[PDB]
Amino acid sequence: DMPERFDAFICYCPSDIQFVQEMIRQLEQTNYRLKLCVSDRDVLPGTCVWSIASELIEKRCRRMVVVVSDDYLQSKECDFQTKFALSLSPGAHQKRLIPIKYKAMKKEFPSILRFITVCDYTNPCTKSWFWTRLAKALSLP
Image 1 (cartoon, helix red, strand yellow):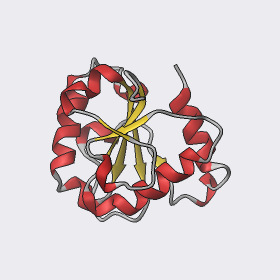
Image 2: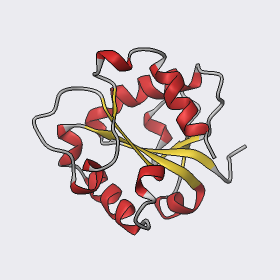
Image 3: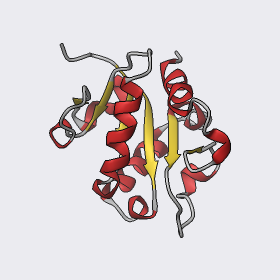
C-alpha cells in the first residue's frame, strides 16, 4: 500500500501538469520502480503517484523534483519549494533538489536553484536515455 517513504516528491504548478504527466509516465516505464508523491494525485489519473501531506515531505521524501518554468516562478508552489529549500543545511541542496526545465524561459532561476545543477530537458545533448538517467539519480541512496 502507501509507502512510508518516497524516492521523490514532485513539486510543480498547475500550468506545468502536462510535463509532469509525461515525466511520471516515462519514469514508470524505466526499470527503477520509484516511489513518487505529489500534493494531490487526483489530478494525475492513470499514474501510480501518491498524495502526501505537505508537512511530511521533508521527513518522508529523499529528494524533491522541481519543475521550473516562467509560470512556476510566479506560483504558490515555488513559494513552498523556496521555504523548503531554505530549511535545508547548506550543502544539502545539491543532493536533495532536482530542478528540471522543459521549455524556454524569459525569467531567471530563483535564488536558491541558481547554484545547483539543472536537468535541462530542452538540451539536445541530454537526449540520450534522459528518463533513465533521471530515474537512476532518483534511486540513489
